[PDB]
Amino acid sequence: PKLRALRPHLKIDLVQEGLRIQIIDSQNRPMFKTGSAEVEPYMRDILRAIAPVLNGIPNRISLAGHTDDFPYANGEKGYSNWELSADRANASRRELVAGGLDNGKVLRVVGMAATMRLSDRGPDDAINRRISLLVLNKQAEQAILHHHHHH
Amino acid sequence: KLRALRPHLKIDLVQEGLRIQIIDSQNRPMFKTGSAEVEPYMRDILRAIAPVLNGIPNRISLAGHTDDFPYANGEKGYSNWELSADRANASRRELVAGGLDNGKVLRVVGMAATMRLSDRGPDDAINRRISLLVLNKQAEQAILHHHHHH
């Protein structure tokens, strides 16, 4: 019934590095109030809903935030998309943990700002605001583990 | 600044490029405990390397490492995850203040206490560090390709 409402927000697909779960915004429905890193009610439900499922998968997670709220012609000297994307990723992280997801599964939190946007400013830029959960392969995990021992 | 920063500033070469690490010391932290606002000394170092980094035509990834909060608990609220991300973003804002172009920043990462180098013994100061990674073109494309489906 309400799976029609999840359909334009929950984007699941298989990626080389593993299982990517994207929670994207709509024109009429955002997962976060514009400029805010506070979880919207509907966003709260989705994260607590997939948390018990993800906890059943023996693999670890990487969280990445994407946001288009603040300008990037900004110069980004104060609170920008970098802080916002990182905060929204961590906000999603806290909800997942509250949903029953073991905290030990979290491996990385990433702020992407708007560097990975798909649309320009306009009636389509809702897709630029998304949270990406990446359930990693054992090989992809080993690569990232290795990379951040170099970082 | 002969040996005022050299116990704090480490520079080494890795596969992905040039890694610039800013490490805490036992008696001189780069951030006050639990806080993500930059210390007066941190601000100086960051603005001292910002103009140099701006000269290098390569882009940068920021990463923070923290063990201020207990990872043995549930990490249900504000934890090392938020603190490491905020400290990375705080270092980021001090870099653009030092004249570094914001377009050079490619990624901000919180790693919490995952990449911890030492248990909470005598000198566990190394567990608290900010890592600047100046990426070569190969590593930059990889990270771009990776996050393009992340």
Image (spheres, coloured by chain):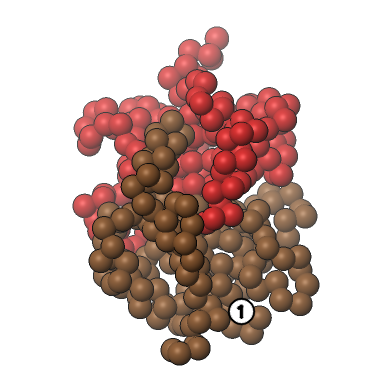
Chain colours: A red, B brown
User: In the figure, residue A56 lies in which quadrant?
Assistant: top right
Quadrant in the picture for the N terminus of chain A: top right
Residue at (32% x, 36% y) in the render: A117
Q: Left or right: where does residue B119 sit relative to residue A39?
A: right
Q: Left or right: where does residue A48 sit relative to residue B150?
A: right
Q: Residue furthest top?
A: A1
Q: Position of residue A75 (x, y in %)?
A: 25, 58
Q: Name the amino acid type tagged 1.
A: Ser
Camera sees residue A77: yes
Above or below, comparing residue B1 to residue A91 in the picture: below
Secondary structure beneath label 1: loop
| Camera-nearest residue between B94 and B2 | B2
Q: Mark 1 highlights which residue?
A: B25
Subunit of mark 1?
A: B
Residue at (65% x, 37% y) in the render: A60
Residue at (32% x, 67% y) in the render: B53
